[PDB]
Length: 97
Length: 71
Image 1: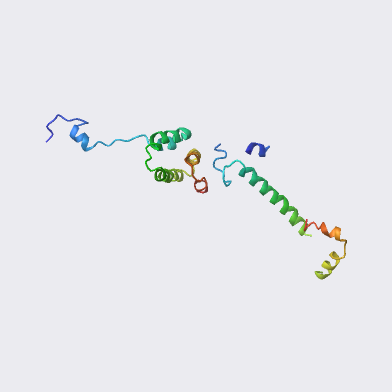
Image 2: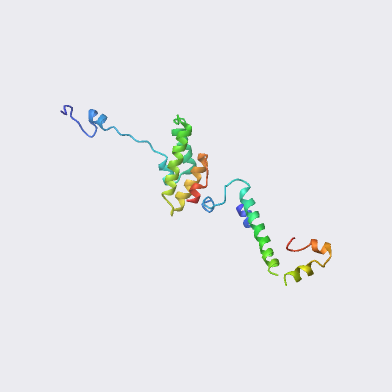
């Protein structure tokens, strides 16, 4: 029963489908915005990282996935290296790949 | 250091061990030294068995101390 005149944002339906998203670091990395990539990542997440070790490991896994995704392209690889270095981890797995 | 030894994406995708301050030139010097040695090595070592050893044992001790192979 849609009593209220609904639209592209019916309040009950809007709750039924409220699915928001933030500009995840993939935006900068995939573009290739290194220093801004790390900095915005920290701005959003470093404080938000209630589990700094766990969150750091997860971000590293994401970084490795992203890097592996783009073997041929040069720019993506360079961005991957820089983001790994700014992360604080090893810089040989991605380079070896 | 790369430029001086020669004397971005160019580099950050090469495969030296780590991008630390020293390791780059350290490895460059090590590899160059090993090559410059082994080249002269094979050069010297490319140069009767018992007879040859006997003759090589008949020289003066200071001369033998400067055996290029031993050197």
